[PDB]
């Protein structure tokens, strides 16, 4: 029996990605896609888990995707400011504003040294 | 019976093995055939003991990635432990280096940042070279420029003191930036106060 | 003593004593609220020669806990031993406490010896078949094999040998709900014990002495 | 023999023969056991039968066991206070955190082939 052709904004193929890259994805507004890191880099996330890293491409503005990546430490930006929400092991969340065309870090490689988790990635 | 070249193989182990196997090799090499048979019987276990020590040390001295890997490795089968020591440990090690470089970028100056940035996007070998020497070279360049700036933007005493440090050694420039420029300020402040 | 754990208020007159910090330890039982009966060998330098165990203060600080069936709880009373009164002939000593425990009754003493074939029980804080030191006290079952000059010979029934730490522990014989002390454990083969092995379950205990206790407690 | 507790580790004679480890005196609340899903405090060395486990019956507890050329310890659900001694007779104390792994001399900061002297449970 066929499924309904309804958009629920649940990241397509998330089940496969969980198995392949180790990253997991939830809901977003559909304007950010997971892709390869081979000359098509836009927003890039580095962690010590899964397959080490992965890239996302912005299709339109504004955009957001509530993906989850354990033990994240570094973010690359390009041609856009990026607003990132991370959470500590005690459940407390904070917001870090990363400048365009630059590189910044998180807890682990930041000021606290905490093994924080990436909660929300938002495009200005 | 023993192999005709059994002693030669034992010397080989003596040269390249760990402390355990090496000491055991000495007994076989200095003693007779019985000492050799005893060595060979235990050698498969002695190598394992040496392997555990190396991993156990990494559990104490490595970074978050390597320490965790080593802590589990020391409880694995002999074959699994050697795979870890031979190559498996390398990935955890690379990850620890990536984080340290990232940390330096956030804290350091333009020189350190540019060098670290390049290191992160490069190879494991390049990252190691940056950590081993490159970050120090980069820091020195940042220090030199800061002194040069003080030489042009500070007050009379700050200007002169920076000038002397600038033509000296890296060590002189660092001492100036950490302490000497503060003394120089105080002197500029004294001058202004007395003059007023 | 290897058997079921027991914390019931039938054997709450028992006691456990320690001499020094880690020097010696053994079992005992109350004969009065101020007096606890144990073996003399517990206070001997040489446990196989309890001849030098003189009357007077203990050589080392000695403490005893009474009624504490379960060592992981505060239930029970703690008292210090101030004076010892050794038996003139056999391995038996009465320990005088600094303070009374009026809440815990003593065990009545037997009027005579048990004979061969008589079903006796024993309780103590000694080693088990699988534990060096137990949490709770245990009760075993023994039978009399023979009676000798001032002592009773017993054997374990279905295993259950007297082991280590049982010295000073009571040997009991009940009738119609009334418990009488018939003797005090001294030596054993220690079969079926943690950390050791032997086939024999045989043990020997000093015969209870009602007159010795009476002329000491009421001295 | 007399049924008196001398606090000498039961079966220590057989352990020396079988595992190579030796045991002396303790408060009786630590037992030597196998390492098969029942692990509590585990000791590793390069002698005897490589390693062995101990089970804590009650707290506090102690056992002055001796293990030549020791290099590491595992802890679980409890902090462990460990005393080790160097080849020059000097002893030191290392406090190992619960649910973690620590090393000694050989695999520690000094590289010395130290000996385990005392294992104490908080």
Image (spheres, coloured by chain):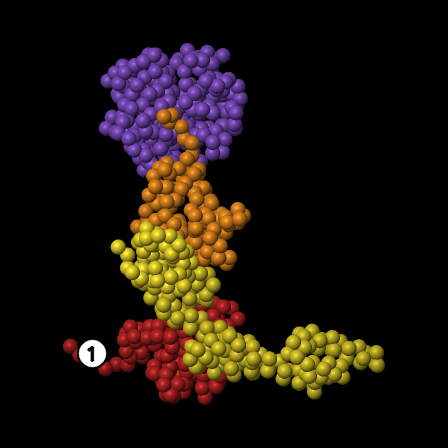
Chain colours: A red, B yellow, C purple, D orange
Q: Residue furthest right?
A: B195
Residue at the spot 44% in from the left edge and 37% down from the top edge? D25
Q: Is residue B77 visible?
A: yes
Image quarter hosting the C terminus of chain B: bottom right
Residue at the spot 50% in from the left edge and 18% down from the top edge? C54
The answer to which of B76 and A50 lies nearer the viewer is B76
Residue C159 pos. (x, y %): 25, 29
Vertical order, B40 against B164 (above or below): above
Q: Is residue A24 left or right of residue B134?
A: left
The answer to which of C108 and B165 lies nearer the viewer is B165
Vertical order, C88 against A44 (above or below): above
Q: Is residue B72 visible?
A: no
Chain of the residue under the numbered disc 1 shown in the image = A
Residue B42 pos. (x, y %): 33, 54
Residue C168 pos. (x, y %): 40, 23
Residue at the spot 44% in from the left edge and 61% down from the top edge? B57
Would you name the residue on which mark 1 appears?
Answer: A3
Residue at the spot 49% in from the left edge and 48% down from the top edge? D84
For the image, the number of numbered tags is: 1
The answer to which of D100 and D87 lies nearer the viewer is D87
Residue A122 pos. (x, y %): 42, 80
The answer to which of B128 and A8 lies nearer the viewer is B128
Q: Residues within 10 Å of mark 1 (few under 14, many from 20)?
A: few
Image quarter hosting the N terminus of chain B: bottom left
Q: Secondary structure at mark 1?
A: loop
Vertical order, D24 against A91 (above or below): above
């Amino acid at each position: 029996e066929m499924p309904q052709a309804v958009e629920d904004f649940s990241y397509p193929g998330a089940a496969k990605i969980q198995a392949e890259t180790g990253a997991i994805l939830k809901r977003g507004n559909g304007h950010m896609l997971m892709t390869s890191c081979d000359g098509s880099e836009d927003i890039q996330v580095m962690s010590r888990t899964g397959q080490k890293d992965f890239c996302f491409n912005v299709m339109a503005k504004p955009a957001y995707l509530t993906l989850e990546v354990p033990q994240a430490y570094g973010i690359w930006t390009s041609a856009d400011p990026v607003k990132t929400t991370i959470k500590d092991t005690d459940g407390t969340a904070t917001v870090i504003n990363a400048p365009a065309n630059d590189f910044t870090g998180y807890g682990e490689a930041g000021s606290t040294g905490e093994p924080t988790t990436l909660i929300e990635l938002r495009v200005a | 019976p023993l192999p005709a070249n059994v002693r030669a193989d034992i010397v080989g182990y003596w040269e390249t093995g760990g402390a355990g196997l090496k000491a055991a090799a000495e007994q076989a090499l200095l003693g007779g055939d019985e000492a050799i048979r005893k060595f060979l019987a235990d050698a498969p276990s002695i190598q394992h003991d040496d392997n555990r020590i190396d991993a156990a040390r990494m559990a104490m001295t490595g970074g978050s990635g390597l320490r965790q890997a080593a802590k589990d490795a020391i409880r694995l089968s002999p074959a699994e432990l050697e795979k870890f020591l031979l190559y498996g440990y390398e990935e955890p090690l690379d990850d620890d280096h990536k984080v340290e470089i990232a940390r330096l970028i956030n804290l350091g100056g333009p020189g350190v940042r540019e060098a670290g940035k390049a290191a992160l996007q490069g190879t494991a070998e390049e990252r190691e070279l940056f950590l081993n020497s490159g970050q120090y070279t980069a820091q020195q360049d940042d220090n030199r420029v800061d002194v040069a700036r003080l030489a042009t933007t500070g007050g009379p005493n700050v200007q002169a003191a920076a000038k002397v440090a600038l033509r000296g050694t890296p060590e002189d420039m660092v001492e100036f930036l950490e302490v000497g420029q503060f003394t120089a300020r105080n002197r500029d402040q004294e001058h202004a106060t007395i003059a007023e | 003593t290897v058997g079921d754990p027991t914390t019931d208020a039938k054997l709450d007159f028992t006691a456990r004593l320690t001499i020094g910090t880690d020097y010696r330890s053994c079992s005992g039982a109350l004969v009065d609220t101020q007096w606890v009966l144990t073996a003399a060998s517990c206070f001997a330098d040489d446990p196989n020669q309890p001849d030098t165990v003189a009357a007077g203060k203990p050589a080392q600080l000695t403490r005893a806990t009474v009624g504490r069936a379960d060592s992981n709880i505060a239930n029970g009373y703690v008292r210090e031993v101030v004076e010892l009164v050794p038996h003139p002939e056999r391995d038996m000593v009465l320990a005088r406490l600094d303070k009374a425990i009026p809440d815990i009754a003593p065990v009545r003493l037997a009027s005579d010896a048990p004979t061969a074939g008589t079903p006796l029980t024993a309780v103590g804080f000694g080693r088990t078949k699988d534990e060096w030191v137990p949490i709770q006290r245990h009760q075993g079952a023994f039978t009399v094999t023979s009676v000798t000059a001032g002592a009773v010979n017993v054997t374990g029934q279905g295993g259950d040998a007297i082991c280590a730490g049982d010295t000073g522990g009571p040997l009991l014989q009940d009738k119609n709900g009334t418990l009488h002390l018939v003797g005090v454990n001294n030596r054993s083969m220690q079969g079926g014990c943690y950390g050791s092995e032997t086939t024999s379950t045989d043990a020997i205990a000093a015969m209870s002495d009602a007159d010795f206790v009476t002329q000491t407690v009421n001295r």
